[PDB]
Image 1: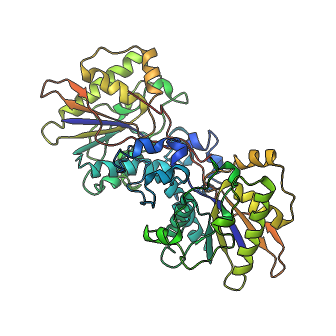
Image 2 (image 1 turned 30 degrees about the vertical axis):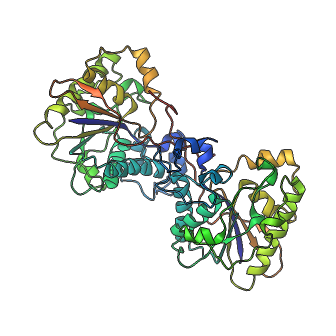
Image 3 (image 1 turned 45 degrees about the vertical axis):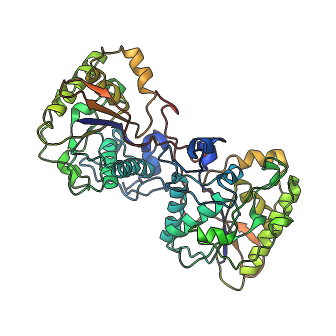
Length: 255
Length: 262
């Protein structure tokens, strides 16, 4: 029926900088917040807090951005039946807070899908980031499904992949996600990255894939929690872009 | 100890959505139809209709949240607030109200609306002051305002298109009046007002020399929303000095991407 793709919320490493860990972790590794936009606590990572370097969480206003989207979906009576998300912490946290706003934290389990991760050229680093596994996510108070079997596993991701690769696996996973939810529920929410909003949806329309230049141009346009929607053309296998069921979310900075 | 806290209002509708945010939000009949998640679900009705919003804009949803977090931080630091005053601008009143909610003092503290805390009237467009909402109408619209309170500088005493050092002066007098009336009835005072107010209300209180207008404006434009400065007094002396704020600062960025799509 309907596919909703949206981008994650505000990130710590963007608002507070590349050296943000020095602003919230002391010598002994204790978390000490220095700003009201930093969350009261952060999950423990199986490996230490330097794993946050490559996999930063969302800010307190990131949680709000997500929650308002959640609440907006509830106010418009848009029922989400399954939620998928990228393995990035920021994406999981965004997905979780959308559910809080949806009043469905204790009825839906988020399906962490590595195939939804962004184009690996934009990794700020040499290797893939250490992601927090589903089991360890659930224990950090994020509503994930430890049962879920990913269509693309972590090992299948090529470090520093190419445009054609990324676009291809984006299409496969979306197609796969669309298949395994046909029998169960009407609407599907993907919570992922700016790139995901374009790559995952381009062929869904039946329109030819735009080249990498016109794709970067399209990706820089998407805001935090930027939210798009696709409707199924009867049962034709092509989906067209609909007007989203909620209003857009715009705000400035502190100044 | 005895502290004075001065903080700027939260994010404004007319900055985020522009001078003509009304044309977006209100239809021909005067019905409020929000077009963004950062717009509140409703707005208070005004005496002269929605066109009164032109020069007295409300805060945004994120503006409300900013105020809420600051209130919650104050509660977490165990900072008791005994009195709260605000500029008569709707944005300041609403900011103060949401600070009280985070503080869990909505139904205990009553905000004192004080026209002398209003910003420099040179920044008001036209040759006429904003159609402010009176305290009685404010209470009726769910903002914990003190209807009893009698302002030190009423609306009629405000000079339209006033000069810098006049603004500087009345800011100084009003702060001193506010301090003086609260001396016997408690310790900590919160003032919720404008960017200019942080330097204006506290400069000469600390004996410091006010800056000239040009240097003043430059400083003013750096103060973030809910920017929060603090002053402490040495016992019963009337000598005030700057102190570290008893809460953390608040910083966040914009929504990003494009402002307009499709």
